[PDB]
Length: 68
Length: 63
Image 1: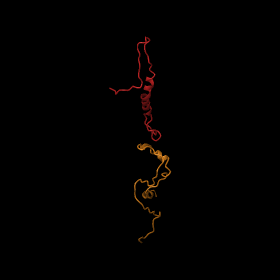
Image 2: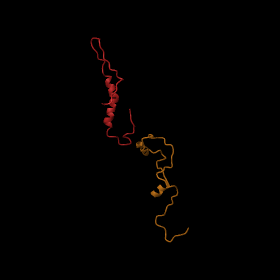
Image 3: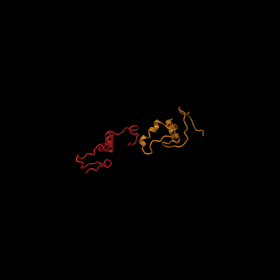
Image 4: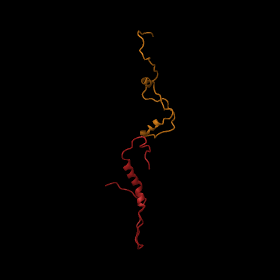
């Protein structure tokens, strides 16, 4: 595939291959602490004290492309 | 008794819990702890006697 006339634009392009999804958390394990099965008003207490694997949870590749 | 403990620790609590909790605590325990203080009063003639059973009280639906 060789079709081009002028040089590429200044910021080099990034190739993001994967699956397009909305608000997906792949890395899931068993968290030691749980905060009530029904009341979701107190679940935010698990964001101040993450389970050490969801401390910086990555997501889909579309999220990475958008952030980039 | 205690409700969901994480109230005021994860959300702003309702601006009613003072009066509401006070009245519920009163109804739950003060009635019992005041009815027990009611004496076993009676007459000096050794002829009559009045008693107030404590663990039987209840309230009625307002008319």
